[PDB]
Image 1 (spheres, rainbow over the protein chains, first blue to last red):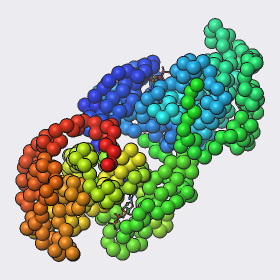
Image 2 (cartoon, each protein chain N blue to C red):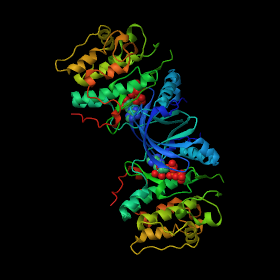
Image 3 (cartoon, rainbow over the protein chains, first blue to last red):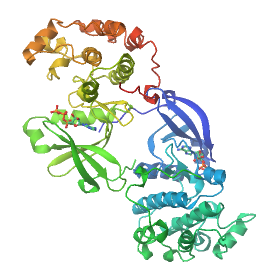
Image 4 (cartoon, protein in one colour):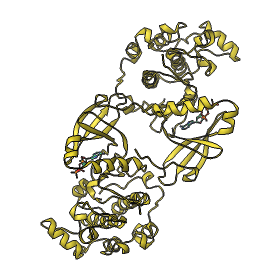
Length: 285
Length: 285
Ligand SMILES: Nc1ncnc2c1ncn2[C@@H]1O[C@H](COP(=O)(O)OP(=O)(O)OP(=O)(O)O)[C@@H](O)[C@H]1O
Ligand SMILES: Nc1ncnc2c1ncn2[C@@H]1O[C@H](COP(=O)(O)OP(=O)(O)OP(=O)(O)O)[C@@H](O)[C@H]1O
């Protein structure tokens, strides 16, 4: 079926740089014909080819095109000129979830519960499509103008077919033990990251911290971390059921019978899971 | 490039009927996996085939798929089962513009100007793609939750290639004289409808009214109508430059040098055309 004409650089008025990565730069752009604002990720083809990143850029596009859920950054269009590729993405006006963690120090119980629930809901959708994020972190969980989450950064995701993996290792503080021991990744690897994120929301800092990566990995494989006295009891119990060395024993994984038991955890008692994105997010402190 | 899986009836929880047409019924539906609300237009295949409406249903889908502008109802997806076709459309929460005309009687100058400007902007986009609506009317100009317009009903549109036409005749009160005399339609036919709509917004009733269709057509070809004393002066001048029998002399048409002169009309003096959908619509009385 016919689709709109392929867009081009001239159709936009580019503005400020929203972010810079190793193989891309995201720029805020206003489409002239509609006045719509998009976050356009620009990637130089030559650099991508030189560093053998074609599989990653291709995967990012393919995975995003398959996602159709309110808690994920949307890919509206793509186009390219002689030197660059352009991905038209939804513009998450409020930035990274990490920004708010730093801004207010830590989230109260109500805000922790709400945002954790949205992340859990997003992961259920993602995992339901046999996709592993592999680099889930506050930096990758953006916030739209209404303060609902919008997860992004899928170039390093893993699309399951069988849960084999290997090759990529996400941000050190959120790396699961299986990636360091067996060099493998599965859906449960994301649940481990979830556990670190919940801990970070409540404590204000991720569970495993150290002077360098080697030391962080060392703490991870030994499950070396502890909870501060204040930590919300039910949240602590949940984290303990997520930060489990054995990937088959993490609440939410297939061997633990899926998302049902996870969403039924006491910490989420007052959560209505059916329409989170229609709910008004609690105000951050 | 991969796309989401084809949706199906079971993916939705259908609700109330939003509207009923001769070959379709629009139903409010909530997608289970996202809690998103869509207005799903359902059309029975057998009926469509019996009445030879395949060209119309096909055109509706094709035209909508080509539109990517904030002032038009969006087509998100399509699917079908053994008996029906389903079009997933954006849900215009506030209904038809006609509803508000009846609700408050008539629009003040500020509201008339704002909504007329959005319609003009929508038509510029539509015409820029060589598409003639052919049945533009308050009933076809919906309003989203933010009170910005969303034009719909494209099955009877005409996609230009050369401005030939003929075959279909829209709602009597908005029919242009060329359709009644030469049995032809062009972009300017929509501008005539625009003139009737502006008049209706200000007067509260369309320009040409009568007991039946024959009498309405009779008044149209004779340009038989008049303005009530109150009518905003500049709005009147604009309408007089739109309701012109000769289609090549309507403000906004190609022979009159396009949308530039139309948007520059005195009635729109204080209008900023670049970002109308980013502006807060004036409150209706
Ligand atoms: N859709 C978006 N809306 C608003 N901001 C965004 C969006 N996408 C990305 N950003 C911002 O731009 C930054 C850079 O994104 P990009 O994908 O180009 O590199 P990165 O993934 O952050 O780093 P790298 O790819 O090297 O790991 C992000 O960290 C984020 O702050
Ligand atoms: N996207 C939408 N969102 C909300 N309401 C809608 C939407 N589309 C249509 N409607 C409502 O449903 C009604 C019926 O639409 P439909 O296209 O099924 O028939 P119609 O075009 O109104 O009549 P006919 O096709 O016989 O001329 C519309 O008049 C409008 O009131």
